[PDB]
Image 1 (tube, rainbow over the protein chains, first blue to last red):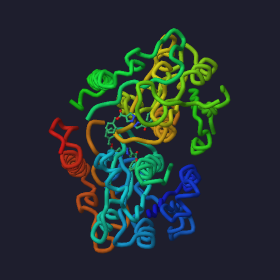
Image 2 (image 1 turned 30 degrees about the vertical axis):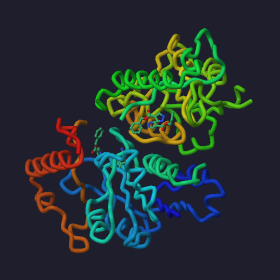
Image 3 (image 1 turned 60 degrees about the horizontal axis):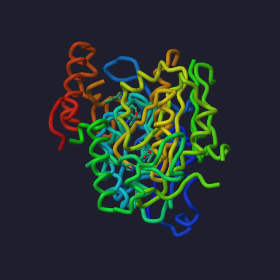
Image 4 (image 1 turned 180 degrees about the horizontal axis):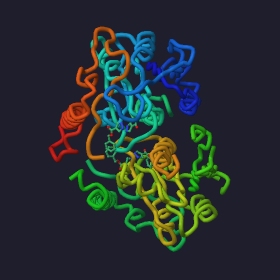
Length: 213
Length: 204
Ligand SMILES: O=C(OCc1ccccc1)c1cn[nH]c1
Ligand SMILES: O=C(OCc1ccccc1)c1cn[nH]c1
Ligand SMILES: O=C(OCc1ccccc1)c1cn[nH]c1
Ligand SMILES: O=C(OCc1ccccc1)c1cn[nH]c1
């Protein structure tokens, strides 16, 4: 079983992934995704979640007092606290695999500029904390990254959602708009098909991801 | 002004997207159909999306000026540089695949009349392109008129002391040159720790 809690100032953003869990995995008690409005933990009548950065400059920084209260309530010592940010360690398939066996993920969605560093630093003294990036680009907030993380992890959790690059794939029909499926794939020579696919993979990786070599 | 069209068999998942400087439309791929997928030629696990449905959908939605975007973990990397580039496009069409992918002939065909970009938003596997579409849309739209190479170091805000943890004193000093130097140092230190590849070093 896995419990996932997402904390965000835009709770409805996570509606698609909550309303995407098969009834079977929820009823088997194997997965539960809860979404929490960060403003639940604000202290002032204006429900402030951010403030100006120390040391100046434009941008806003999310308040440590608000986040601290939220995580105090939601997390336990067993929690894996995931903080998406473009400044994080890379989140990869290996990460997805590892987190797929966790009992409790809490995902703290920050907004542009980010969360006061003391929030993660404090949490790290009593739980495992992971600042991660899903890719080298900047979003306005962590919510899309949370969607990506939840999907990549949960699809590795048995029955929940239902090296080199992979080369091109083909299916019916055998001919379409003047383009034939490569005849080797229809040859019934499965050793040859494997070797063809390996070369396709090598060529595609060289062309698109030479870093992987 | 930009138009973004998203094509998907799960249009509900694209609810998280004024309009004004951009218009975003989401289209149900099934509006152009039996099934949308079948087993792969040459064998293997999973299903491949048939080219036929996609062809008709893209014929209606795309023009020769369209930038066709296809999220896939086998794509060229989508980075901040890509986002800057696409931020000046008139028309993005994002083809969301499911299962093992879309028949390659869809992209090959589209490429004879428009520019096509197969892209990865990162090295992991999703069940479908919808989440990636959301990521791309966000990354692009915040760069659109009227809205790297290092990791940013930590940020702080009030109070100056919290749970016995102080904001770095230099940030309270009002000395802009020292604040600038400290932040530059924190950025480089964080980058070498978390992303040594960005500074030209071997990954862990
Ligand atoms: O933009 C992202 O997260 C939102 C965020 C969080 C903190 C500060 C700025 C922006 C992101 C990019 N790759 N992975 C995550
Ligand atoms: O090309 C693929 O894998 C690329 C990959 C994935 C994860 C980490 C690194 C590289 C692929 C295509 N469909 N499914 C997987
Ligand atoms: O999983 C992704 O897209 C869905 C997809 C599309 C085609 C085949 C398999 C999976 C993706 C990962 N990084 N960038 C995109
Ligand atoms: O650390 C950051 O950017 C990292 C980044 C971005 C884009 C490509 C590579 C790396 C950041 C945090 N808040 N705003 C920006």
